[PDB]
Length: 183
DNA sequence: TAGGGTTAAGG
Image (cartoon, rainbow, N blue to C red; front, side):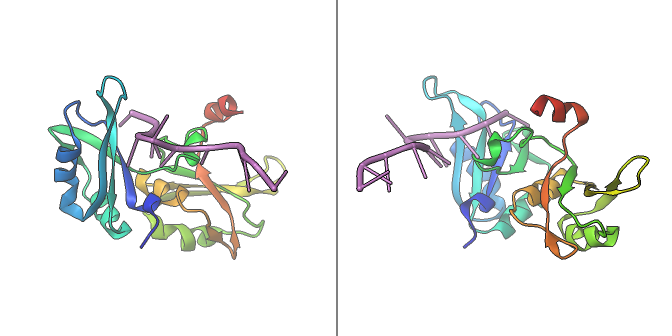
């Protein structure tokens, strides 16, 4: 019995006419749904254009994501790992990114260290261990790029990540400008 | 395309 948060998917871009029933009829093809709902405006009752689907196990969530692209009621929608209400308050928590910031890695951390932990989440395209300009000093963080945005989401929703023997913090990478406006 | 009357008491 895995946590409800990890068994749930945010479904974005829903057609205006998709309902709890039609959404369920589609996603039920990859497993048992324990919850399925279309979010709509309290007053107008109008669909807000998104919803959530929750499966009995994360294995079923994974099958659902492996089946992208998904078309619901004639509309290509965008399935995403559900980000908790708490983590949703963070800047850029809902961005569709392929790169993650990895902070707090030992100075002697090498690429194979990052691969042995991250490759399990998806195909890695780029690994950059950051150093100081002119100094050459290791700065204690790195960037890892995957070929699927879901590899990143699968990672950032977990709390701990062990690299080169110790825990490190992992977040979605923000651009220079996204970083500045977030400060 | 970010949540459903789902987030700080009273000792």
